[PDB]
Amino acid sequence: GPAVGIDLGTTYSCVGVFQHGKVEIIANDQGNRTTPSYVAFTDTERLIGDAAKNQVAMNPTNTVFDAKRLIGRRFDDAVVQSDMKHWPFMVVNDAGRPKVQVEYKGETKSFYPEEVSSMVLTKMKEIAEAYLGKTVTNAVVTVPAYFNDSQRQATKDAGTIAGLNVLCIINEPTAAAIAYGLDKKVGAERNVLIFDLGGGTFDVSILTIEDGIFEVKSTAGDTHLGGEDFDNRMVNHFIAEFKRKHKKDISENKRAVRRLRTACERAKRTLSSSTQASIEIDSLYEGIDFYTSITRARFEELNADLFRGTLDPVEKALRDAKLDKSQIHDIVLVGGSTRIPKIQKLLQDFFNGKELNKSINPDEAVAYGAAVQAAILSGDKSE
Amino acid sequence: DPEKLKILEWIEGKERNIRALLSTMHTVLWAGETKWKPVGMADLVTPEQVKKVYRKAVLVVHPCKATGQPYEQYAKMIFMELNDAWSEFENQ
Ligand SMILES: Nc1ncnc2c1ncn2[C@@H]1O[C@H](COP(=O)(O)OP(=O)(O)O)[C@@H](O)[C@H]1O
């Protein structure tokens, strides 16, 4: 029956379905409504999502992630070459096309970036099928607004490899605006700002809406700013603490630092609705239990410059859109980091107390909108 | 406007009759459209023929291909009326 919406995200992916009058954002078998865009290969299994993410410390070189950054690209792309340094997995050259080389079941294997993204997509496809009790084929998949044709065609190709028929490739900030029904309003054209802060990237797009038609007037942001960086500012806080308490540097230690990063991401989320979080790691480094505390005030202090600095791309987007901030009619909160109370305040203050569209889990908003659009592009939504 | 009135008159007279809509869709298409040959009733008798031509119609007017185009608003309108026509045809 139904067509689904899939947010194919740099760090997390999310699938939703328009069904029986509502959009349901669908939890995976672990209970999670977003799913890491991670593929891990071991001696015995190909792991996707959480199981892949949870083992990245014991198996760093064979846990692929960040394929969205390789998709639609040539190997000799500046961006590919820059980013490669940061990854623990190997990226090889297959006639001007990036591949990822891994060890899977004793053998060396390489995969194209759309093949990795196809694995994530297959995983999301199964999540929807488990919920719906039938097979899913038709889907709308989303991409960043700045994506070119080659990147859009590669994302569509990823769907086909996942056994999906892709009804459309649509832009992320547009989906989020569809989630809010911003196009179902009589009157003069509306300027909409999409403030989107995920796990790896920061996107600000301004959009005009009149008669249900969308155009992108401007975009800005930082392809290397997201919740991961706030996690980093936390890791090093605790690397330093650990050292003072124990006279040991866990910094040489790749698995110790990875294990602390997970602890840290977990506490950061707790800090979005509570004012302190506990860190609790058994045998972090050479047999030492690491238990500690962090407050929201402190978390915010360690990130004060990156939080505040998300306002530059906003200003920049407005001046490219040739708009003063008071000419923005709707502001939309997207990406799981927009849950961080301080981020909320700083954007609102900037817009002089104007109320922010956030009633929909910001990390689910893109998938929400893709679900709406998938129903429409089928005929599951009339009148 | 003249382009929207056209399609809204087209929908009205044809009474959600898929064959009637298909055999006259060429009269409401945007000037510029070349991918569509006018189809007579001769090619709309059997449900095979309706289906085959319907699946050819929705490709022309798909809202995804039409995104950004000056005619986008009209592609949407025709798409939606055809989807409803076809679902009425399936239910028969
Ligand atoms: N409650 C929370 N508080 C702070 N950050 C969160 C919370 N929930 C999710 N995040 C962050 O959102 C990021 C992922 O956002 P999301 O929009 O899902 O990803 P993507 O950017 O991959 O589309 C991660 O950094 C995650 O830590």
Image (spheres, coloured by chain):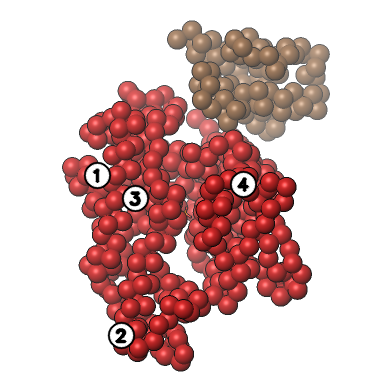
Chain colours: A red, B brown
Q: Chain of mark 1?
A: A
Q: Chain of mark 3?
A: A
Q: Residue furthest top?
A: B2
Question: Which residue does the image show at 68% across and 48% down from the upper left?
Answer: A97
Judged left or right of residue A333, residue A126 is right
Q: Residues within 10 Å of mark 2 (few under 14, many from 20)?
A: few
Q: Residues within 10 Å of mark 1 (few under 14, many from 20)?
A: some
What label sits on residue A1 in the rendered view?
none
Dot 3 and dot 2 within a common chain: yes
**Eyeballing the image, is A217 above or below A53?**
above
Judged left or right of residue B26, residue A307 is left
Q: Which residue is mark 4?
A: A76
| Closer-to-camera residue (B91/A126) | A126
Mark closer to the observer (2, 4): 4
Quarter of the view holding residue A177: top left
What label sits on residue A355 in the rendered view?
1
Question: Which residue does the image show at 26% across and 59% down from the upper left?
Answer: A304
The image position of residue A336, as x and y in percent, is 40, 56
- Disc 3 marks a residue whose amino acid type is Ser
Q: Which residue is mark 2?
A: A244
Quadrant observed for ligand 1 in the rendered image? bottom left
Dot 4: what SS?
A: loop
